[PDB]
Amino acid sequence: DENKQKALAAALGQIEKQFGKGSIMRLGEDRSMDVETISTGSLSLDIALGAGGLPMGRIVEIYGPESSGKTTLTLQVIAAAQREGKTCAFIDAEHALDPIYARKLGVDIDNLLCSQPDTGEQALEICDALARSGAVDVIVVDSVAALTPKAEIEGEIGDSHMGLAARMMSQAMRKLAGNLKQSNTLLIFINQIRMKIGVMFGNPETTTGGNALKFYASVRLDIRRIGAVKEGENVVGSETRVKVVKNKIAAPFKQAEFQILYGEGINFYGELVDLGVKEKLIEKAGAWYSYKGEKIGQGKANATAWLKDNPETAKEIEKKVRELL
DNA sequence: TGGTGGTGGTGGTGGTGGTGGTGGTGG
Ligand SMILES: Nc1ncnc2c1ncn2[C@@H]1O[C@H](COP(=O)(O)OP(=O)(O)OP(O)(O)=S)[C@@H](O)[C@H]1O
Ligand SMILES: [Mg+2]
Image (cartoon, chains in turn red, blue):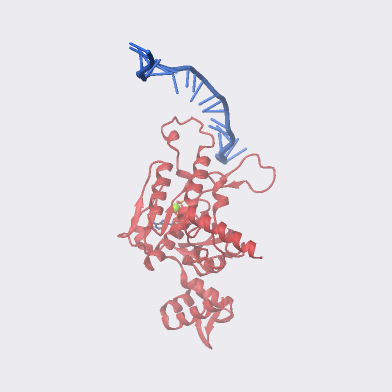
C-alpha cells in the first residue's frame, strides 16, 4: 500500500543522495545495460556468436596451440575497428609482432597504439591507465603466458614462485571489470595451452594463469588448424575451426570454419559462397555451381573468383543471406 | 551623661583495548 511506496521512496532518495545519481534504478529503463557488438570479420563466426559480433565493455578470451592463427584474427578485429572510426591499442607482451604483416592485413599503423612491456604488472597498469581515460576503444594483450611477475624476473632460473601469476590475474580482473564497462571498451586476452599431469580421466589440456580469467569472461573461443589449402603443389593457406566454448549473450556451443590465406587473411568471399550454397540461395548441379539458371563455376575456387570478379551479384547474395540469418 | 563599624580566596587528578587469509604447474 502507500506505506511500501513511501518506504521505497525514502530508501532510494537516501541511497542516491549518498552515492550519487544513477546508483539504483529499474532494469527496463536503464540503457547502459544493453548489449552491443562489432564484427569479427568472418560471417560464420559472426553468426555462431548469435548476437552478431563480440560484446563491448566485456572481456573476451582466445586460445589454441602454436600456429593456430590467434594474432591474425585479433588483427582482423582491430582492423575492422579502425575502419569504422575507433581508436585501438595492442600490447605485445611476447615481443613478436611484425609491423609489415599488420599493414598487409589492413591495420593503419599511423593510429594503432603499441607497447612492449617488461613485467606483467607494467602491462596491466598500462591496460588500466588506457581504459580509465575513455580514449582507447579496443585493447589486446598478445599472450597471458608471458606476463611475468617482477619477483621472478629478478630471481634465479630455479626459484619457484608458486601461484604468483594467479594472484596477479585475480587482482587484475577485480580492478578492470568496472572501468571496462564504464568506458565501453573491449579487452581481448590471448592464451596458450599446457597439458596437465595426474589426470585420471578426461582431457589434460589447460590454459595458463589460474582460474580467475575463466569466470570473468563473456566469450571464449577455441581455434584450431585442420588442413592445408593448396595451389597445385604449392601450399597457400590453412583451414581452421572454431568453437564458442563459452558464451553469455547467446546460446553457446556453435561452430565456424573458414580459410586463412597468407595474404589478406580471412577469405570473406569463400565463406559467403559456402553460406549461399548451404542456405540454398546459390544454385548447384554436380560439380558445377550456378546462379539464377546461369552456370557460375565448376569448382569452389573458380566460383569464388567469379564472385570476386562480380561485385554486382555479390552484394545481392550477401544482403540476402545476412537478412535471412 | 552617651557608643562606633566589617576584611579577603586557594590548588588539579588518571589511561584504555586488537583485527583478518591469498594463489597451482608441467609431459
Ligand atoms: N608475416 C607472415 N607472413 C606470412 N605468413 C604468416 C605471417 N605471420 C604468420 N603467418 C602464418 O599464419 C599462421 C600463424 O598465425 P599466427 O598469427 O602466428 O597465430 P599463432 O597461433 O599465435 O602462432 P604463434 O604466435 O607463432 S604461437 C601460420 O600459418 C603462419 O605461417
Ligand atoms: Mg601470435
